[PDB]
Length: 204
RNA sequence: UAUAUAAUAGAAUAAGAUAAGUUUUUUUUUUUUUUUUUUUUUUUUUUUUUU
Image (cartoon, rainbow, N blue to C red; front, side, top):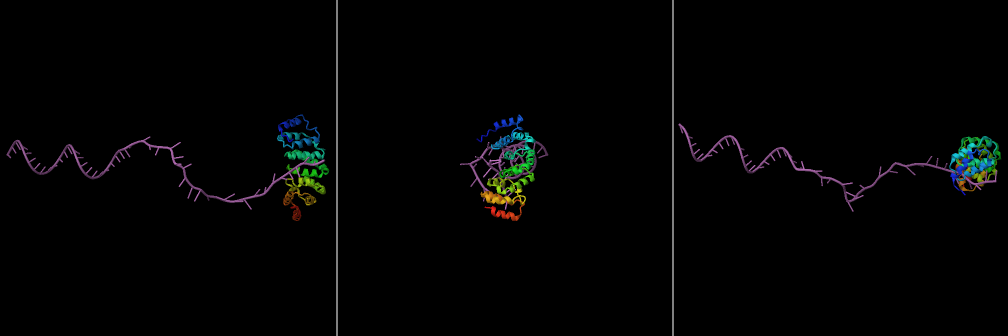
């Protein structure tokens, strides 16, 4: 109902952490609660922060990827940049990155870019995984990836970008996105020949 | 097995009439002219005294 009554939800979110019930909860329930709290633009951020801190190391060690992406998306849309939880997410993503679907990779890239996460090697490995499945990407994933804030830094290597560049021209059809990607190409480390050739078809 | 992301800049320079909001001696000095009073000098007239 998009019912904004945050002074009521604050009581429930205080109870969740007062009774130490934030640790035994199932991961999927957490990934749904936080995503819902990121839908009405919750205000009392400190309570959500204390809720995030409670969950221990054991829980993050073996969470499935599908609730993990929901949790990171809820953190990003809530504009949270907790330091010691991003390292947990980063090292946990090492073992399950192959299992991510193309939509999940597209979501994760921009969700991490929007929270100021600066561990370059994990974003590079995510970009490599995305380029591996380049033929398997649809329009929505292209919008979520190429429309990310500051994607120019993630266009670093030649072999990690070209594999998806074509698909981008072939599939997406909104002219605004075409001009956005054409403008973003100019601020990377790609060579001039490749940039010129890509913009020869991209702009339109 | 998902319904959705959005940020780039430049300049140095002036006109000009609206029927409006106090008042608190008047006096001192210098020069010229006229009138009145006092003093001094000269001339004329009258009276008294002396030679």
